[PDB]
Image (cartoon, rainbow over all chains, first blue to last red; front, top):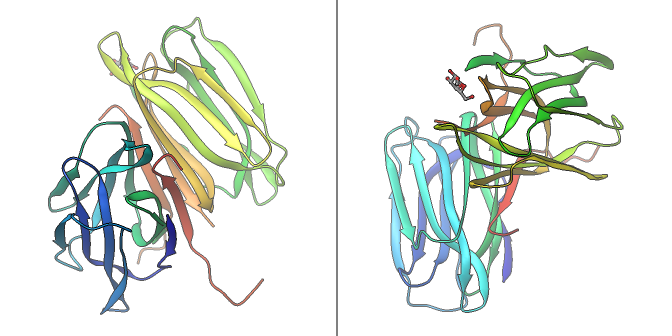
Length: 133
Length: 133
Length: 16
Length: 16
Ligand SMILES: CO[C@@H]1O[C@H](CO)[C@H](O)[C@H](O)[C@H]1O
């Protein structure tokens, strides 16, 4: 996969991702907030194409993500993120993809996701999140 | 179960917990650092006996936790924390308990666990961690 | 603000 | 120190 690292911002306005229902999460792009202005993040694309695109448009600043969760599993020999769900104080977006494999979740009691990093090959291999008050 | 919330400190010196290889995590207690003095956290005890005690004494400050992981699952009709494992930059402590049910994990690329909170009845029901740079 | 300092908290894991 | 500010990071998930 190709590594990526957006760094840290001041919050999240929009998540653009893609997935396929037989495979996994494909591409990933975030529109951050930067001091109350939109910052259009790099668009991290899979080496292949075919995925169904989704736009998660949050009602910023009142709406924010409280939990990220997903499944990892094996697709044609690759262990990847097969599913993602984003739960905010307002509602749940997802699951997008295939919800089979080993689960993971990052629930947040206090604080904000303010950036993403990770790696994408054919699919989303893994990701980390920057957190801040 | 009975709620506990130790608050936030400067770091972690020692974790004392108990577990049963057929059930789940029981007692939990932490010796934090507070500006260079050990802060002896309240021993948060299970309602029941019969657990095995473990002392995780860390080489503070050069050694620190990088990943907490575990399983959650049924015991007696309750969803509880069935196992924990603590990985530092120096070694791995655990798994302690029963490594069955739903996996979870919190790996940390940057920052420190500085506090625990949660609830313990017969077993560790749930927990959260305070993070700081 | 209040005069109580704030910290990031992640969790909970276990029972909901 | 360096002059780059820092931020808590948690992860990775995705079989690592
Ligand atoms: C069997 O007693 C219980 O212990 C459980 C498992 O830990 C839960 O905490 C219950 O609330 C507490 O009443």
